[PDB]
Image: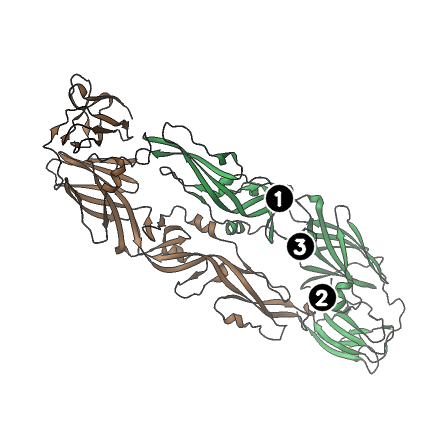
Chain colours: A green, B brown
């Protein structure tokens, strides 16, 4: 909805003594449901999302080190100690340096040595937990009633589904209502998944993969960086010195490891929602309460015009925009015929029974013409609009 | 030099009728050369370096994108174009977007679209060419003459070598001279090698490895980043937009790919030189001009003292520092004996013929005592110093 603007589009016809029509809605796709003596119904999968997930952890991939302190003791003089050893925001390591007269000691041998450094995570990845019972999914539902493309967004009904809302109605005034009984298949995940976020990017990742990461992590909710040694490297001691270095930025390596994982985006307006770039919806569509309006309205006889010529949609259909100048409440007659003389229509009309509601209005018509050469005819009498069309595919 | 201060130490002795004796000097190691009736000569490999290598290339691992511009054209309206498409510091991409009435075009079908962005390398790795004949290497040469450790550095003779020069002398006052005829074996490779440096860290890498890196590169002199697409991703077009992104920082991945490669450091106060963390030097040592000083001295008869008690060096040797307050230009008798009464020496003296030149002088003596229990006896008479010693290792 509207399916004309969407490239990947499927037309579905049901038996018309058919009440339900099952259809599947995939991402970036759309479905036009057509039923005889019934208005056409565009449905499309808008979003499959997760509403405000619990941030479980943070995983540092960029860390800097400051205030490197070291305490050293000569052989047989005892075990070394630093005060920062009693501080969580410091990474420390304990070793033994080869010491003697060369480096200011009394005895030759192993001297205890400790090195500490202040750990600051510059950049981290957030890991959110995912509950299956948090999934909302959205379906656009719209009727073919001759609305101009500029009026599509305002005419679209947005149907939101939960683990509780699984049968939604779509009410189109004057045309009744349609009932969607839908069900989300979000591919896989859950009982073994995280929402991993790096700034603006987000993915669905495996929990065991994320917990086996050779990177420092942090809780909710704050606290301390766990396993800080994954980004801290202590070079072997020399006399009374130890070089402490932070490892390189692991952004690119992580992102490389995240190729193939399902993408996720957080949205900016407005709720912290996590839209999945996957999954699909299986719906049951009830069309019985859809009534074809133009329930009355004489048909407009007066000379009309093509505001927008018949154009190929790429869907095997054609779209037109016709203006009705002297047509106070009108019905637009539209036929597609093998030739002008034989008025035998063979075009299946998508915009079923089009209406010009107001004095001087412009209506959008969509028709599915037969293969080969044909004639798109709009109106009757001498002011019949004709437009020759060809179909290939 | 001094080999007592260096843990990894090898003793090499030459024959009596020997002028020349060959030895190999490795990094962080040291060699004590011993010759009968001749002072022991500590040699050590200090550095193997390259002075100002030629910068061959630059490889960007951190890139930012600015000034993202986009040009789009409707179907059958022609090819899209940006001026920035013909600018060198910009990454551009040419594609086709699915367009129609849905996104404000007149026809349904492909519309040509261009996306450009200003490319700025935030961080790059420098790649230097290295000339095999500019390798300079430095060797410390020092004699065992009883100098205290605080006077070691001042007594060390520093010998600088080049690719062709080649043969250096070490002249010690009172003890003659030694001649080193050395040759640097720098392991591998050169000619097909680069000095790759990131910030302060540096390595020796293969040229073809660096040229095959899936990263944007540049020819130093002047600036043009080639293959920007290795750090730029243009997501598939949607309507009239293409979002252009910089990839993540590739520092950690590069540093990981450089694990195992030989390390290099540039230093600050030998001034911007690239020391190899590898290679070794093979030398021929001429000892013929080495004279044992003070071999016509009288014996120290007088009460001496231990300024520094005999301590284990970790080399299986012991070091002592003895004061000679009253003795006048004499030589210090040093023996290690299985018993005090029969004072029969079984310790080989590293400090061959230690002498007290001035009264109240403190001499550093190193002895290789026999295994097990022994008696370190220094001097004669009732005031001969004794120190009972134990050896295992």
> What's the mark number on residue A182?
none
Asked whether the residues under marks 2 and 1 belong to the same chain, the reply is yes
Q: Residues within 10 Å of mark 2 (few under 14, many from 20)?
A: many
> What's the mark number on residue A267?
3
Q: Which residue is mark 2?
A: A4
Q: Secondary structure at mark 2?
A: loop
Q: Position of residue A220 (x, y in %)?
A: 62, 42
Q: Secondary structure at mark 1?
A: strand
> Which is nearer the N-term, disc 1 or disc 3?
1
Side of A238 relative to A309 (left or right): left
Q: Which residue is mark 1?
A: A193
User: A383 above or below B56?
Assistant: below
Q: CA distance from mark 1 to mark 3?
A: 20 Å
For discs 3 and 2, the disc positioned in front in the rendered view: 3
Q: Position of residue A250 (x, y in %)?
A: 50, 49
Quarter of the image where one finds residue B39: top left
């Amino acid at each position: 909805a509207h399916c004309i603007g969407i490239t990947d589009r499927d037309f579905i016809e049901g038996v018309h003594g058919g009440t339900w029509v099952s259809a599947t809605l995939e991402q970036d796709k759309c479905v036009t449901v057509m039923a005889p003596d019934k208005p056409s119904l565009d449905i499309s999968l808008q979003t499959v999302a997760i509403d405000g997930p619990a941030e479980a952890r943070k995983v540092c991939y960029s860390a800097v080190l400051t205030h490197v302190k070291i305490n050293d003791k000569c052989p047989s003089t005892g075990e070394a100690h630093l005060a920062e050893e009693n501080d969580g925001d410091n990474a420390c390591k304990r070793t033994y340096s080869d010491r003697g007269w060369g480096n200011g000691c009394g005895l030759f041998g192993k001297g205890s040595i400790v090195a500490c450094a202040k750990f600051t995570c510059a950049k981290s990845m957030s890991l959110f937990e995912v509950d299956q019972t948090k999934i909302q999914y959205v379906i656009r539902a719209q009727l073919h009633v001759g609305a101009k493309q500029e009026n599509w967004n305002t005419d679209i009904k947005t149907l939101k589904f939960d683990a509780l809302s699984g049968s939604q109605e779509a009410e189109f005034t004057g045309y009744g209502k349609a009932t969607l009984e839908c069900q989300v298949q979000t591919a896989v995940d859950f009982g073994n998944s995280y929402i991993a976020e790096m700034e603006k990017d987000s993915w669905i990742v495996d929990r065991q993969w994320a917990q086996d990461l050779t990177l420092p992590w942090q809780s909710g909710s704050g606290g301390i960086w766990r396993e800080m040694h994954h980004l801290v490297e202590f070079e072997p001691p020399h006399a009374a010195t130890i070089r402490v270095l932070a490892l390189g930025n692991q952004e690119g390596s992580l992102k490389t490891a995240l190729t193939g994982a399902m993408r996720v985006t957080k949205d900016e307006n407005d709720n912290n929602l996590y839209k999945l770039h996957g999954g699909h919806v299986s719906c049951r569509v009830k069309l019985s309460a859809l009534t074809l309006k133009g329930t009355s309205y004489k048909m407009c006889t007066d000379k009309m015009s093509f505001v927008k010529n018949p154009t190929d949609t790429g869907h095997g259909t054609v779209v037109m925009q016709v203006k009705v100048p002297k047509g106070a409440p009108c019905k637009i007659p539209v036929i597609v015929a093998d030739d002008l003389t034989a008025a035998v229509n063979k075009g299946i009309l998508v915009t079923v029974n089009p209406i010009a509601s107001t004095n001087d209005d412009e209506v959008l018509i969509e028709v599915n013409p037969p293969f080969g050469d044909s004639y798109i005819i709009v109106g009757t009498g001498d002011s019949r609009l004709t437009y020759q069309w060809h179909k290939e595919g």
